[PDB]
Length: 102
Length: 102
Ligand SMILES: N[C@@H](Cc1c[nH]c2ccccc12)C(=O)O
Ligand SMILES: N[C@@H](Cc1c[nH]c2ccccc12)C(=O)O
Image 1 (tube, rainbow over the protein chains, first blue to last red):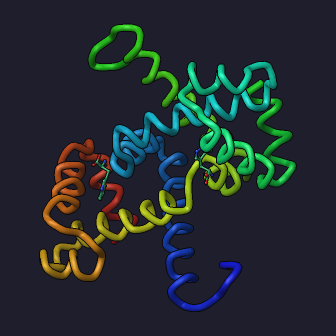
Image 2 (cartoon, each protein chain N blue to C red; image 1 turned 180 degrees about the vertical axis):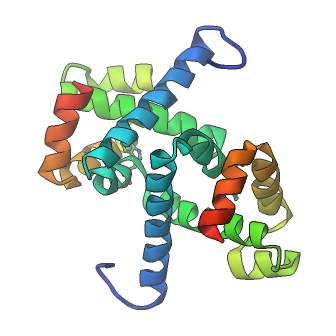
């Protein structure tokens, strides 16, 4: 699975997959909310909420550098993270976000 | 929604819900993996993977304090976080995890 199959890496990788599957199930059972609440800190949840917006406004292409930073709290670093992260996503996600966010 | 409806709080709260819904959709479209990859840092993913284990072993009731800390990296604080977090979950999640993790 992992781009570097060792045993430790692979393990960490599988544990992540185990989380994904857990969640998938949670959704199927309408237990997603409470699960995510359990698994994440308040601050992490808040951060996820914000990243959606950052992702949102990056796709939109209206908000400027100073705008992102001052209104959403995104400076060169964060906007760098968000950006390359967007470039790294397979095109299908990028297409989907367009339809869905926008 | 929020246990303290203001405007700022509620807003933050809704943004989180917007994330939940996004993800729900992603799952429905088989775009969950790439989405989560986009939305989370490597370290956050790793942490999620570990929390599953911590949650796992807390439910199981075999692993001791020293064991959790030394094997899973969980000291009094983390095990405190994990614990009260478990107590805070509605009983339906607690029941479900039993069936599913165990
Ligand atoms: N996948 C991103 C996670 C993240 C951090 N900050 C963000 C801002 C916007 C979107 C995603 C992000 C990265 O690993 O760095
Ligand atoms: N909901 C937990 C998130 C968390 C932190 N560390 C954990 C360890 C195990 C399970 C959950 C957690 C809390 O807010 O603190």
